[PDB]
Length: 62
Length: 62
Image (cartoon, rainbow over all chains, first blue to last red; front, side, top):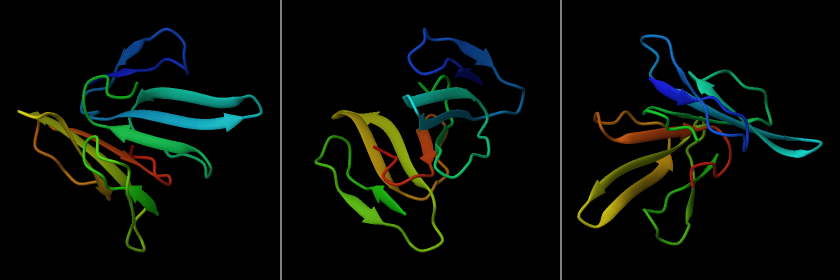
């Protein structure tokens, strides 16, 4: 699996996940400065108030 | 949990999920009509090739 791993609106970047990993994630929240987007491989545990989306296809998390 | 449940490009509609349900899903494939999107509560398994995204926040599955 290949997932995007770039932050917010930064130029797209990707990363090769570990073998067996089928998911990518999109973690969104707003801090004092508004919306922030984090992306990567897997489907991590997230804090309350954090919007988490997990998808199962190549670079599905933009 | 509230999730969208409208198909493809129809007007947005929502559904209140069963208690105990915290996920919403977006399932996408294609047919003669174009890109088909199914939305709902939960996080189903899909046939290989079908794009699936699951999210854990209100109306997160547009």
